[PDB]
Length: 113
Length: 115
Ligand SMILES: [Cl-]
Ligand SMILES: [Cl-]
Image 1 (cartoon, each protein chain N blue to C red):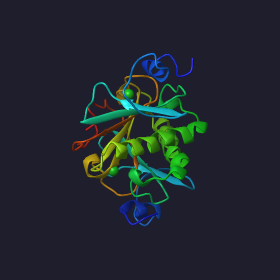
Image 2: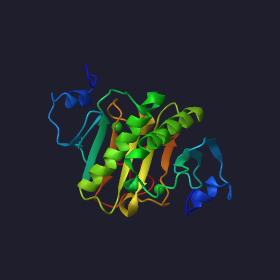
Image 3: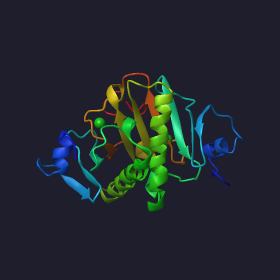
Image 4: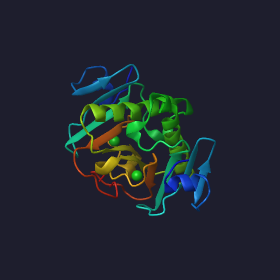
């Protein structure tokens, strides 16, 4: 679903440790985890970044968050976690395919970067 | 009460002043009083949800609406170089108010990891 490494993951062309899939999104462990649990939830629709998401995408974006919180519960994150979406250079976005980070299993600190 | 018992419920009902950026029937965006970036605001639902871990399946559109309002407000505030959106869940997430709230931070380089 797109012209990035995450499109290749969606198409199963390169491996990832997949946590959950449905017809419109995919959740998988981050290859460079920043916490004991660190996974991504991505749409299969290639939205390059949250700044270009459309109004009609609202329920899809909320679906990523609902999938994210369900996966976090399944992975035992009962003490809490942090969800992150990066936009652009200042946001530290590393792949131009919208992706929701879910980090847990340790105390997350403030500020969030 | 509409909006709940937390400080964010009082902000929704105009009982406590806030610096409001955007308001509609489903959510409210306002500046954080303890900013962690040159621009730092929150987007909250007007419906009280204590935390993301108890959000219902039917809350999908509302949660997505928070991010759409977040990115529109970021553009209106001139965060053209980018920004970071954050939702904190629970103790390990650093959640400070138990009313779902999306943080939007920008105006400086954000670092990795995100806390
Ligand atoms: Cl990213
Ligand atoms: Cl919070």
